[PDB]
Image (tube, rainbow over all chains, first blue to last red):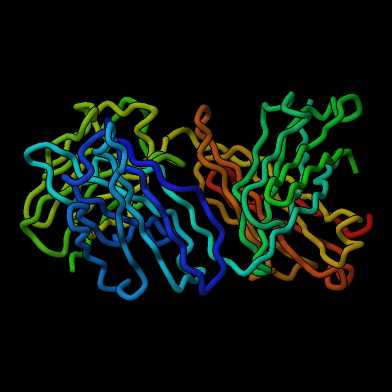
Length: 227
Length: 208
């Protein structure tokens, strides 16, 4: 089975270059081109280029020329000589280059052309920002009173993504909505986690949101009670 | 270059029904490719050469078309088929069509949350309005402070469509400096939604 495995997500400062690797295995690496494509938030897919592993011949999207370089390395293992790695280096990054980058390969059937990509790497997220790593502040969204009430935690001003949020250490899951984070104009992210519960319980049950931001090594337990 | 225009932007249907999605190319005569991208998952090839199914793609996916007009038909929709679908020709791509789950209209439950004293102590005020468990996703949230409409100072976020009850939730967050917050009394979010016979308002008076 064909397998394309990329290097992990990274945070890059504007002006940086990023080098992404794509380890390809389960077929003869020299026999198929690898393409790179990026999925950009609110803009969709953009083809970056292809490389043909035999000679390492390449073709770059006209609009990216000067900023992209593709190379490859062929296995040097005598009993496992047919896999290889494709590399794509993307330079002069700006926030507009914040995207998920994929390496892809065509299908191997008779009517498979070059562009229908049957095989995809798991993607590599690249975030381009000048923001400094920072753990979140956590504030309460307090329930204001049979009926049902809502409460939550406001997780503010952290970088980079992600933060994880549980309630009562995972014991509370029914009715939890943890929203997609938003990027604020400060360059820092923010999100809320909310949960609906019986008004009846507000005096009997304790509600604690557990916030974890690994990039800053920040863990917070925030107890939320009626205002 | 080739420009691919997909429609509709959003298609709302129920499990068991058949979806038809369209892709119009700016140039005729080329074959069409389709991909499926389920939320948060790697894109998956569905159709190539206009009508050929890719590896492991079930026969309820049917690609067709000719000239500039191309179609993806999904028969007897399965829960997993609700995803975004993209068309491609060579290095060119459509912007995608979202297939979403149709269900009965549901009005949102609306809640408003004043900023905490702790956050205020730090110079900023976040006011949050929650619209919980509604359908369809389209809703208008308006912030009013002492009856003045607020614009440019709030951000919205919307959940993914719930996998089990097909509803959405939405939060709107108004951000003000502490000084600005403390100059006004009435903070209100007005919600307009198909499920509501008239707009619903939740509010509070600062410090009350």
